[PDB]
Length: 289
Length: 290
Image (tube, each protein chain N blue to C red):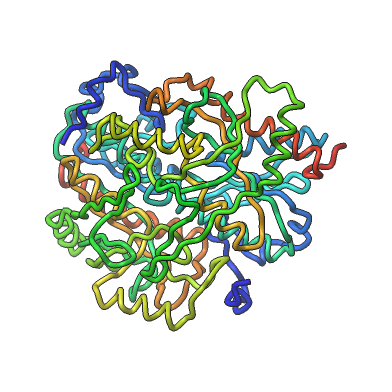
């Protein structure tokens, strides 16, 4: 526990627009055992509603966050829902403020679930990838930080037991997609760091792009996104667990452009929740009314 | 200065803005753009676009050019583009790549990017506008670091100092509710630990070490800290454009970490960069005064 927090009479969650004086955290959040996150406030809101209907609830799924807040926050039974924007720094803001919230509420050993979108490597678009490791662009299982101007690295740890439970569950469901277990690269850029040729700047050839991506695949990487190393390093360090459940929107061994229709992208992006929603129903995420 | 691979594409999809090169005639639609105003919030930049539309004497609503499912918004008022960029360098780089590609297809040359942000102050009172005269990383280096194909790359940051000086001069002739300050700006990849905050969920340093880090920053001329500057000011230069940062402060980090000001006053402070830049754009052919 960050000992400095106890020196505060009131702790302001700036990016969620409330403070420790806004509610009684233990009463309001004490029963939380799952935190579902993704880059889109709209998608995670819709997922929250879907879980509320699964739980047989008939009550408004209200945003707990302030109206001018950067992030949204919903609660359905034992699950918190929040967005995290795009990129490690944005995700870290969510992680700091949400893990503090869990601390004030007395929640222990919570499972963070990132329901994301990603670029696939050697899998068909629309595939769900269950990350079994989260690595940087050098394929190292670490998140890098620069703290007080000094280099710091934090190891990434995926909850492999839950990953295997999810894979097994997928074998007993009727998903119209494949579910693959594999490694996941997190990058600080959508274009150049992910080896895309179609950014506004590109200093490499398709041959060099191919060598980079094929090497990743040969090391077991099956998708690529922008938050995984932050989520799977931070949670472990604050005493919680984390997994990534991300759908693929393109096969990067075939192209860079996201060419699938807006409707198909939206459909694809709901597939992680389709799997995880059933998982939550079977593991006390919701009360099955 | 142009990525040759773009010409391989019959159609270029701007994924995070939800349109393509086939969606409009980019030359016709965007060819007159000479300014791009950005910040972290879609709401704040829309409201700024609206106030510029009023200044330009337009009565019609400012409508989103981006697709409805898009990650970012995009507005246009006369010669000015408006877009949000989320929080952090990777988010900002996505906006930067797709917008500079847009400017390329439209044939726009030498465009000024203006980031209208919020930040933590160093030795200045909350609500102060800082005009960045340099953007540096947490090691106080004027570079943005990237890892491309797994290899380290560094790109120098370049601020349009002429425009900065003009903005300082302009502020001296306006009745602003706040002070305007020229100084250096740190860009960090974290709101909490990388900015030396003691109130994160994790903290591996003491108050003395924080102040030692911040005092060193101040002594190197740093006056505020935010999360996108090194991306904006390295990327624009490299694609043939100019960039400046105009950020208000929401806290004096030499005194504390918590943002204690009310949400309303924060929103008020956050409009102050646009208060100054709005008048600048009016006086420099950003809008057509009708």
